[PDB]
Amino acid sequence: DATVYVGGLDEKVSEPLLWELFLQAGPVVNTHMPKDRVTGQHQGYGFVEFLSEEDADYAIKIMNMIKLYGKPIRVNKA
Amino acid sequence: MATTKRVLYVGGLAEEVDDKVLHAAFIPFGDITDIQIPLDYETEKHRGFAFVEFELAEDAAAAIDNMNESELFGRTIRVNLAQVYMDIKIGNKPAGRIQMLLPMTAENFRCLCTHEKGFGFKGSSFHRIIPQFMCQGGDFTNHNGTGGKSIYGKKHTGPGLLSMANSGPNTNGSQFFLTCDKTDWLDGKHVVFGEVTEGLDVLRQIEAQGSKDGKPKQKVIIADCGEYV
Amino acid sequence: GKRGIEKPPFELPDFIKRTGIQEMREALQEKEEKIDIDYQKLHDAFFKWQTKPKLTIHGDLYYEGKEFETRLKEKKPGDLSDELRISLGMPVPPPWLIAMQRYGPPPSYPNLKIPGLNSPLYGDVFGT
Image (cartoon, rainbow over all chains, first blue to last red; front, side, top):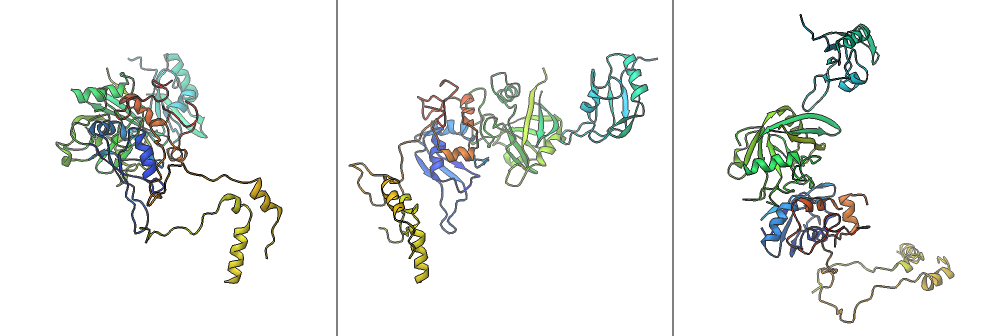
């Protein structure tokens, strides 16, 4: 479970408000939030690696409680 | 021979007149005791007539003689002798009630309807709605997707079935979905645990707010919920 | 290592931008491709309206890139930035600490206290 997939975001969000955002729950050890080079903008889906698995399963339970730009945020195991 | 002279029949009502309008000002003893009217599950809009009950019979007869051919809302109305639930609100409008028939999975959902463990569904939303697929909620204090918690800790043959949302095997919390078609590709991946017994029409009103990407066009709220017990 | 990295030309401070010399220099460059605004306002921006720049520590040596690692302490559980409050849009708990009621205190930060639950809160910071 150490990693999660996160959908439905707005590009003003970046890797930092994800950092800050999910460490509110529990620390994101490895952050991945693609920067698209071609048009220089984000599609808004994320992958998160944690310290171990327990962090991330609690993360499955609590985690789908973040609303990014008035809008819904997908978090599921991976 | 009968004593059913309490329920009065009101006709020629307006599109704005409802059980409330008739209560504070109906034909006989309408606003009093109990009132009946044509209410939908999603639309929840009265036609023009209805039935009002009076605490007594004399009061009802007096209400008819008067309200008879009276003037309401600039119109002439006629008066004469005549398992758990979720109440859904869509935008600012009541849509109606869904009734559901529901061991560990059923007990979790039951407690989340009653709030008997100190938290539950009341006031939460259906945050992901996909037409011809499903309406997902139970992210009570989340309003995302697979957010919430079970009563135990953190963790498809046709329309109108209840099934648990999850984030993989053995990750049930509080999130659930109501199916809007046969969704057999989810068999063996999500735990089905109940069925709609009344208010499939209200579920169709929720589905009407869906989009292909799941974003609700209007807020869909569980205005109230509980158990029949 | 900084071959393809294209950066801005110059980041002037507020004490130089509040004097109007940059717009006059841009107008002179556009006319060539004078002003005489003031003489005491520049002295006031150099003496009274002087801003202290952000210095560094004695052990804060210059790294190779030193621009993509804008690390800052460790904004943890119970403490968030302004704007993300704006996206969240809550007027002065952050609402998923409503679900930190149900599902339990986080495994990741066990020592946690967040307002209103076991932590009996003012401004931004809703947990310690």
